[PDB]
Image (cartoon, rainbow, N blue to C red):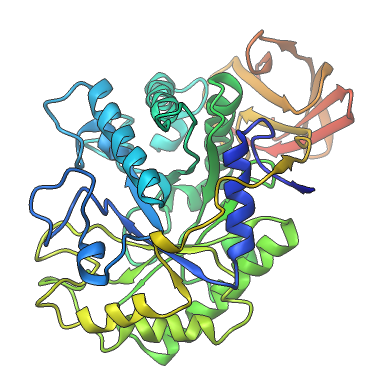
Amino acid sequence: DETIAIVDADATAETRSLLSYLDGVRGEGILFGHHGTTSSGLTTGPTDGTTSDVKNVTGDFPAVFGWSTSIIEGNQRPGLAENTRDENIALFADYIRKADAIGGVNTVGAGVENFVTGGSFYDDTLRAVLPGGSHHAELVAYLDDIAELADASRRDDGTLIPIVFRPWHENAGSWFWWGAAYGSPGEYQELYRFTVEYLRDVKGVSNFLYAWGPGGGFGGNRDVYLRTYPGDAFVDVLGLDTYDSTGSDAFLAGLVADLRMIAEIADEKGKVSAFTRFGVSGGVGTNGSSPAQWFTKVLAAIKADPVASRNAYMETGENADAGQHFVPVPGDALLEDFQAYAADPFTLFASEVTGAFDRTVAAAPAQPVVHIASPADGARVASAPTTVRVRVGGTDVQSVTVEVAQGGTVVDTLDLAYDGALWWTAPWSPTYTVTATATTAAGTLDVTNEVAAA
């Protein structure tokens, strides 16, 4: 008789099971993950989603199979540039099915590449993809494709395969902070929240768990770590991304402090924490480094701490080529150490994953939430009128009013109108604090955004 807080209160049985399993493993063993593990290999030859350098070097597949949404764009195998998005999606789904059949857990991340030059969201492109933005439609279409992938990731018997989905994280560099998100955390929060709401509430995705990791190297400082946190109603798995090539005592101490911190925050929230990304900076190949016994040193530091060890998985990077790869292969100096890392009883691989999906676990009722999607907290409004959008979720809503104040004086009062799909809205012609008050079946909910007018 188990009940858990899960972002999608309507998630499938297997999905709720997975979230329970990931919490339960914390401190008992840590699942080893590898990105594109059956799609890019140095020892596999041509890939088909059934073989892996990890299997060849350790004797087992990883417990976690990582993938990028980049595959849909055909910018990452098994995605092909020459393909229709629909067939890149079918391939993606096929490899996810194969991983599930192997016994692994799937994670899918959406990086922030599209938010730069060559990217399709390219316009301060964070502002651009939010509701009302010049590129909002691109975002929505990108999400539609993700919803398509979600629905296609089904076992032969039709069962949806649960996926740990990590929307909008930075792929550079060694600490992986998304500069735009730190620069405007309110806008990051609205982007993440919309992403969750569009997929869950608008598209009906029911096989996602939602991951968020803001980077790494926080010195265990919680307020820095939480700067871009989307909120308890929006995140299932709390992450941490840290690459290092020194193997130093100092680095290890810093890593342990952060791992303790995320486990502590997870525990307090009744959530799951995971070491979402780890690896040798620059990889362990030609263009990388071979810090001595780096894998077993990292693992021993984690194991030695009863709180830092409370982390569900740790995923390392893609094995692209000799110059850039993150799992050692024959010829690499770190091969033996990685094998030892893999043989350690604390690290879990595919054949050690059991009871992940067949648990009986009910969802706690969704928590009522109110947030102002536009203008986002800390944003700057450009034109008048601008549209105020408020999302009230998880309860029935009778009305929403907005009070606009400046200094401490109310300057405007707005009665919002439900748009029939997602938001309560009203025009606003500025101008500094924007407070939404929703009258609902769960009581009166409010939230305040602080914004600037041009």
